[PDB]
Length: 377
Ligand SMILES: C[C@@]1(c2cc(NC(=O)c3ccc(C#N)cn3)ccc2F)Cn2cccc2C(N)=N1
Image (cartoon, rainbow, N blue to C red):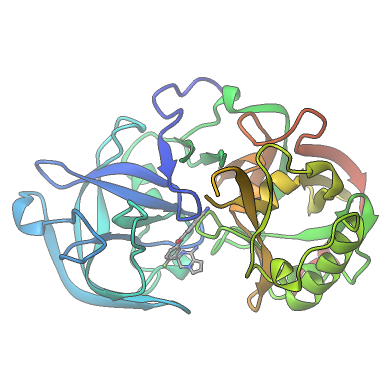
């Protein structure tokens, strides 16, 4: 069920704070592009016209295998938007599963506030399900097509390392060398986003003590396309108050807790131990069982490049659309998106940033009753 996937180890790169990307090729002969790994969307969208932030793009007229689907697509986000032309081409991942598949491609011809200056990615690989694909669910996502066309198991796993950044996307398997300890699995509640259920939250062991529906209002998802741990308004406010109280041996400006200002220390003297750990309990696979994943301040204090000082941004923030377990969560763990068994596994990542005295953790089981109640029905 696990093993060695040696070609896919260390295939992810990124700039600190701008996205984890994998190298892919599109077309014949192959055109190389860096593509953002994104579990919170479902389109394979690539830049396909010049743009000041893109130093290369998909040139359909140079690909003998390109097929025009003759239909536009317009995708607005909250901050940013793009428009493109639908088609297909042959697609590979050079440091991947050693197969070439024909996939749908949204060739981006126009955009605003979508490509990031200096991010070094020219497109996005949306790994979620068809239900949120644009323009609709008839456009099969990349991974659906890869599994149908090859013998690749219906599973992928992500190890995002953090502290420039790097990691691994294992297509079709679970690499045993990227984690320690047990893999603990939570159910995928519904196949659209990768939706999970949080049943309990602690700050340094102290229960936040809310109706567990508040943790999942109106949904809880696992999203590699988001930096922060994003929490509903009522949950975020309770969490910040508890983190303040636990770290009260040092006081910081209010703007730090809003993510608007950096706090610094003399290089090497960052006092990790005064900051608390953060635990999310996830619904288990067995009735009345949960497990918990625990991250450190090394995950939610994110480094920002005086060279003699280490400075950081607080990366827990408020969400209007439910909980988003972003890179802040995922960088503590090796996360298994087991689509075949409709579950998401977590294990202590073998590359996660920590100190001599604390590590990230995945522990279980715990008797948690009435866990279906925690879902926003
Ligand atoms: C397609 C979408 C998207 C993601 C991104 N990602 C980054 O810039 C990004 C930046 C840093 C990390 C990390 N460490 C990960 N990602 C950029 C554009 C975009 F359009 C839309 N969107 C809105 C909110 C969340 C999402 C999402 N999951 N994907």
